[PDB]
Amino acid sequence: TKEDARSTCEKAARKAAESNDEEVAKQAAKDCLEVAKQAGMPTKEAARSFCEAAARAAAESNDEEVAKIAAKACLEVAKQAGMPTKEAARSFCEAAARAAAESNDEEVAKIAAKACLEVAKQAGMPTKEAARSFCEAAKRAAKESNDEEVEKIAKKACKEVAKQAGMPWLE
Image (cartoon, rainbow, N blue to C red; front, side, top):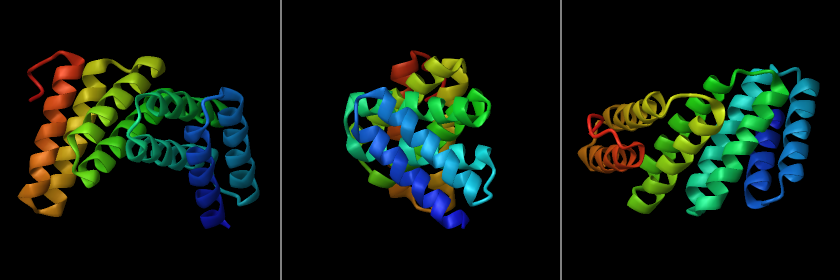
C-alpha cells in the first residue's frame, strides 16, 4: 500500500535525521525505496515524500546539524531513487519553509533557511533559486492560509533567508 510506503519513508526520514551516521540514512533511504517498490509507488514520489518529511524533521528538531543530516539524507535517497537533485532540494526547501511557517518560530525559520540553502549547496542548485523557492513557499503558505499572523512569520523567514543567502533583494 502507498500509505505504508509514505509512512515508512517519513519514519525512515526521521530516523535518518535523528542519527548522525550516514550509513543509517543510506539504509533508511534504501528501506524507503524498497517498501516504495513493494507498495508499487514511484521511487521519485517516495524520495520526494522522504525529503519533505526530512525537511519537516530537521525543522521540528530545531538543531543545526540535523539540518545537514536531513539534507544529505534527502540527497541520498534522491541519488538512490534516480530523482534529480534540483527537484529534491526544491521540495526540501519548500517543505522546510512550510514547516517553518507552521512552527511560527524565528529560530526554526533560521534553521529551515540554513537547511534549505545547505541542501541547495550540496545539490547544485543556486543559493538564489533556493532562497527564492523558500521565501515564495512561505509567502504561498501565508496567502493560502489567508491570515496575516502567518504572513508575519513568512516575512521573518524571508528576511532570515535573505540574510543567509546574502542577497537583500529577496526581502
